[PDB]
Amino acid sequence: NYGYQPLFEDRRPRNIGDTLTIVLQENVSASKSSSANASRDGKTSFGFDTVPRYLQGL
Amino acid sequence: MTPLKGVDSQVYALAQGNILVGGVQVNQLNGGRITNGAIIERELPTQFGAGN
């Protein structure tokens, strides 16, 4: 090989045949949540159990 | 016997010998010169003599 090579540079890959080291160190995490609720409650009551004579009609 | 190489990483000379250094302006004692200390090993091709 007759190509020029620097002295103080970090010897990074520069041509087709150059080799490089890869540290994967991959870490991905995704989360998703959702909730919904709806509650309705009702109760009505009415009773005499004793009706006046004048109100007995109704 | 240190090999002297060019920018192409090729050994172009071999250097070996004795260092000479100077013996308030003190001389540099961490840098010396060797006269005829290196012998060439490779010859660079040239175009001299070709063309007009």
Image (cartoon, rainbow, N blue to C red):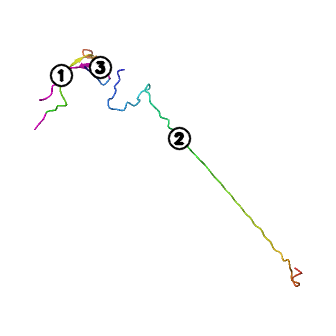
**Chain ID at mark 3:** B
Tell me, yes or no, whether the two marked residues, 2 and 1, touch with CB atoms within 8 Å.
no
Pinpoint residue A5: horizontal percent, then vertical percent.
34, 27
Q: Which residue is the site of mark 1?
A: B18
Characterize the magenta stretch by its predominant secondary structure: loop
| Residue that label 3 marks | B11
Query: For the view shown, which residue lies furthest in the top direction?
Result: B49
- Which residue, given by chain and number where applicable, does mark 2 sit on? A27
SS under mark 3: strand
Residue A13 appears in which quarter of the rendering? top left
- Magenta extent: B9-26
**Front disc: 3 or 1:** 1
- The residue drawn where x is 50% and y is 37% is A25
* Left or right placement of residue B43 versus residue A37 in this view: left
For label 2, count other residues whose C-alpha is less than 10 Å away and answer few (under 14), some (14-19) or many (20+).
few
- Kind of residue sitting beneath label 1: Asn
Position of residue A15 relative to residue A26, above or below, is above
Badge 2: chain ID: A
Give the distance between the C-alpha atoms of the residues marked 3 and 1, in whole angstroms. 21 Å
Residue under the point 39% across and 31% down: A12
Q: Are marks 2 and 1 on the same chain?
A: no
Q: Determine the secondary structure under disc 2.
A: loop
